[PDB]
Length: 180
Length: 179
Length: 177
Ligand SMILES: Nc1nc2c(ncn2[C@@H]2O[C@H](COP(=O)(O)OP(=O)(O)NP(=O)(O)O)[C@@H](O)[C@H]2O)c(=O)[nH]1
Ligand SMILES: [Mg+2]
Image (cartoon, rainbow over all chains, first blue to last red; front, side, top):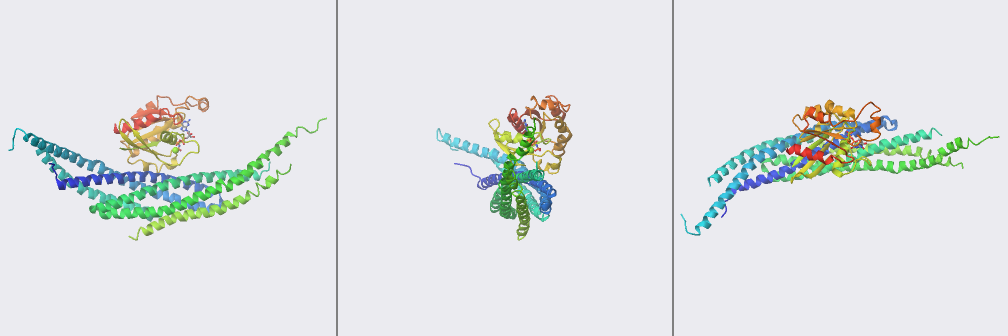
């Protein structure tokens, strides 16, 4: 006695699961941004301590200086990285937080409508099983609305993620190329 | 009193300091680096999963997962090195240097007393005990032997650390091309 | 929900002590703990679960180049200054206000008076009088915020905690409004 739009409901479950996983990648990206920022700074300090020690220690002038230059270079290349990651996080935050929420907002209206329609016919039956009488639009309209949104949403999800994954990957790689 | 020693000791302290402040930035480096691997480990898993579950973006989640993974692998080695760095330097600070700085507190307990008891018992004179130098040897020969150690440990420590950082990026770019 | 709060403001003011006191309930004293570290906190703001991310910064010119890197995706800034340091307070408009805006001209800012204790103590009250200076009164700190657009102005001591908890409870409200 339950209404089921099989294909559509399978897609709604998959979108909820995707948002769940994306929100998770999003949390990791944020942490990534914090830790990267903490690292970057140290390497800067470390770069000074070493450089200082380099001048106040001729016995180890070359050894400290060699490390000071490296910690300094890394710090600089790690600024470009931290930037790229902020862009990754920000971009995906919009997708989940806004684009996906727009659709889900429409998915909730449709489900609410599906359930009230089920309660409606059920009430009709347990009313017929009485003094006899044996002789939907909102649900159907909403059902069509989400079908369209799920389609646009999926198209946009692929473009955004394809670009964000490509660039994030490149940045991560570049933080070794120009660093080598 | 004796200038040389107390100019050698005033420098074993400024040094014990800079190395203490290096030991700090080093513990931090460890911490922040450990965190970064956890996130990277988690990110590669999240990416691998999405890769299997998302055919539309299978390649993109695919290579991101691998990268994050080799990166985590290499990072553990780097972390080993950094841990060794900090530790070793820590030994040269909490022990080797303390052992020298302790025989100095002693030397000082029997340092100003001879210069004091001098200006002191100097007042009583004209009206009408020798191992301050034994400890002296244990603050000159205990000291100079420490500086050779500084050089020995730091020279090696400074180099492993640097090669490790270097290796880190070499191994990365290397393996980050076998694809 | 995830909110990102970054604490900036002339070095020596007490931004780090402000975050360690608030999150672990202990003065950063006793050794000065893990440098360049960041802090977070889970708080119940009116029957609501909030994940509060706190970003620490460096106040010396030398870190000017890699400071804005922590600014992106921020939800609320905390420009700090010491009520015992007139020189700092001035930099609130001189350096901080312009920078934070140079990057995020649309983010809610809140002014804070770090070190509300060393304002009525016997010593800094004399040496601060030895330099021909004086503490920072409510007005001008209250006016500084207004001279800016600060969604709020508060004062606290990481040593006494007094007014500490309110600082972050406000930052959250300034966010979800
Ligand atoms: N009495 C008192 N002292 C404080 C307070 N906050 C910080 N201090 C002291 O002020 C000094 C500087 O504190 P700190 O937190 O390091 O300042 P900071 O703004 O983080 N400096 P930086 O940008 O360089 O890291 C420390 O010696 C600390 O004990 C406070 O609320 N009351
Ligand atoms: Mg600080």
